[PDB]
Amino acid sequence: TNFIRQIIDEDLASGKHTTVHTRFPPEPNGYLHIGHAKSICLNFGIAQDYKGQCNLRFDDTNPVKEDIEYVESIKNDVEWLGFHWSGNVRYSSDYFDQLHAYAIELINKGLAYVDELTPEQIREYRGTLTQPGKNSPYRDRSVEENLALFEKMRAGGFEEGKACLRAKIDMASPFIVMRDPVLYRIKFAEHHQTGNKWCIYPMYDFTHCISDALEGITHSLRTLEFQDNRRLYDWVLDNITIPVHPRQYEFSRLNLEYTVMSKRKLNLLVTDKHVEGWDDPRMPTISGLRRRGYTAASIREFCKRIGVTKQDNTIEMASLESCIREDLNENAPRAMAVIDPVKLVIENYQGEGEMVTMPNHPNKPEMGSRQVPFSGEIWIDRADFREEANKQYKRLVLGKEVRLRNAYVIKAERVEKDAEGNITTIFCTYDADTLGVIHWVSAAHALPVEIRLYDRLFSVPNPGAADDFLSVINPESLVIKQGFAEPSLKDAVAGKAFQFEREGYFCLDSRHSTAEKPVFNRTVGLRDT
RNA sequence: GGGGUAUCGCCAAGCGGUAAGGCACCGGAUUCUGAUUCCGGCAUUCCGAGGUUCGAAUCCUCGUACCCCAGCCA
Ligand SMILES: Nc1ncnc2c1ncn2[C@@H]1O[C@H](COS(=O)(=O)NC(=O)[C@@H](N)CCC(=O)O)[C@@H](O)[C@H]1O
């Protein structure tokens, strides 16, 4: 429960409403991030919890910043998260004609006029946060001139920035938004939905209140930066002929430590090629997390946990991670994989090999079991063998022994180093019938694998607050390793996650895995204390 | 100037009866994953200072900190 849901309960009870109708209205000017997920869960979640409706509307009022690839990727993300919208997908562009007609109604009521102040003068005439603005010398044109001048704008008779439509309100309002807000501006750009039919586009504030109203929206839910906008929102609907007046509510926007959360900054990371793309596994985008291995249910869980309030906040990576660990720990089948391999021979072993059974899930037999190949030449992680080490070290130590996961107990005996003195192969002996603990892979049956370990994109908690956030990127946000996995992973499918015992949760695709050389992304490491 | 928010490290309930929960953390028990699971601990105070009240984090007052607004962006 959150304040907004309680308001809804109140509205329902009092009969003010009989159905709830929300909307998710992103601008297709980039991909969606975990923040947008919070909005998606909120808006669609309320819809299904109350048997209401949630529309998917592309707020496409600015052609030069938008692209068809973005709308495509957005429908994709919303669908992947697990939500369905009301009827067809909607586009603000579907209302250009309506918007144009409503602009004409305002002009007719003397509430709007064509201003010819340059883009620099409008700022000069706007006043400041502490000084009132001043009326434009064109503010009192007659209905007829405005009507004529507006038509010229629509017809392309004005070069960009030479004219625009403004609402006639109050140049001396403490709300800078009421200082004669621009309704329409000229843009000779092609629109991904309307082609070149328009050379004038409606602004956000004008478009949104009308789109919500025509769509029958009952609760327009957005973020805190739009609180000031509410006054203009109500002003517009109050002055045009439209039957419904949706109520607005603002919640705080999500912030995650060690990353940025604005399409503008994320896009910069894409354009300057510092990440592979919007869906790079290190990105806080929804598609990036998906490729990283997060489940749509783990994201819905996270959104549910962080809550919806009016307080500024920055969640910790640990929280998001706990969500993904909870899911995978329960559903991900276990497998063996060695990231930093070192040859280990069991001089004691006779033959070409045998087969040992391993649980597909240690704490869940119902998830079945599988046959895994064991032999005399195996790979173990270079970090699980110490010639000495303290008393805490519970792994392989020269002279001492360790249990091979779901297999035999081996005793390190003789080690062998190379030129620079690095160990090349560890010699051990195994007990006839013996079935800490370390994982392993039979060298002979091992599947060569590329393992991509990921880490926080940035070095600091709040990279957004840095002068040059790019200069604070973590050089080790991605580190690639070549290792060995049990033959079993030969069937691994993209997106599907596995737990590589004693390491973490991994998944395929990564956009790079082939048939010859598979690529696994570390979604997240195991809780290691 | 206007609009907002201040409750345990990070989130977050609480709407006058006198501090939920999650994440994190600290112990202990399990365990062929130093994982998981499982017990136990963790704000005598709710930005601060007065005030109304039998009693407030929840009502009032004066403060203080932080966030958003001066795109023909959204
Ligand atoms: N970090 C964050 N945390 C949580 N919610 C966030 C968010 N960033 C954006 N949002 C919300 O996502 C929705 C779409 O984002 S967006 O594509 O930028 N488009 C817009 O903001 C505007 N076209 C919508 C205006 C409105 O809804 O009043 C918008 O509704 C916006 O409020």
Image (tube, rainbow, N blue to C red):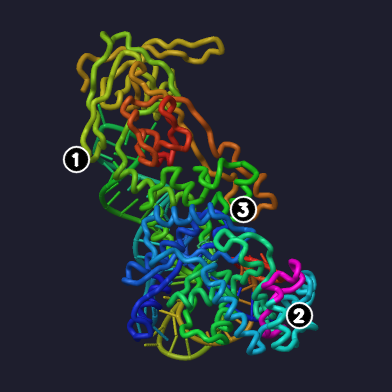
Give me the chain letter of mark 2. A
Residue located at (32% from left, 22% from top): A402
Mark 1 lies on a secondary structure that is: helix
Task: Please identify the quadrant where the N terminus of chain A is shown.
Answer: bottom left
* Residue A385 seen from this side: yes
Amino acid beneath label 1: Glu
The residue tagged 1 is A366
Name the side, left or right, on which A352 lies relative to A165: left
Residue in the foreground of this view, choosing between A490 and A71: A71
The residue tagged 2 is A131
Q: Which mark is residue A5?
A: none
Residue located at (49% from left, 28% from top): A481
Mark 2 lies on a secondary structure that is: loop
The residue tagged 3 is A265
Does the magenta portion include A153? yes
Q: How many angstroms separate mark 2 from mark 3 (CA)?
A: 32 Å
Amino acid beneath label 3: Lys
Amino acid beneath label 2: Gln
